[PDB]
Image 1 (cartoon, one colour):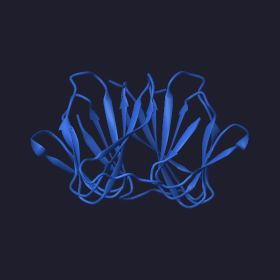
Image 2: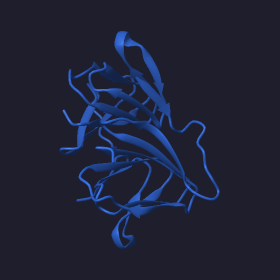
Image 3: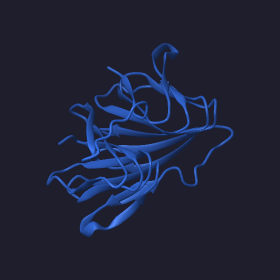
Length: 106
Length: 105
């Protein structure tokens, strides 16, 4: 076991690209955060396997990106749920942090 | 596939916390809980393997465990715990959390 992470207590930016940080990994799920400066992006991708992910916008605003660069607005508190095999990406409009939970883990 | 703006049209109930199913599949169950300040998701556990995570989307609270032990849960805090470890949530301010359970019970 049991533990907490204050994910907005101190965020880490990188001006050249997004920052990826492992929050948790077990047999049950993998939890990772992505911290973006405004305009940065986690490019659209997928892993050709079973399971789903959810992407929760913790801070800032952005877009959930998919197949053909199609976008869903991702305001703070928005959650995207998708199969891991479905192309997904994230684009930050403002400085932004998201949490990704993947189950089962890749 | 599908997105939910969980801080849009937030629903509170004066008498009890509001639980809303976000997503359910074989992989995980995703549920939101919306609390007025002072409301609580009572400490609970199920004797089965798996874990849950609780993400604070808005407001501030406390993650609650065995013996009423607390861990501050500011906005953006994430609790990860076994499903079998006693876990609850207490809202200090009006609060909304997202809970992901894997595998779902």
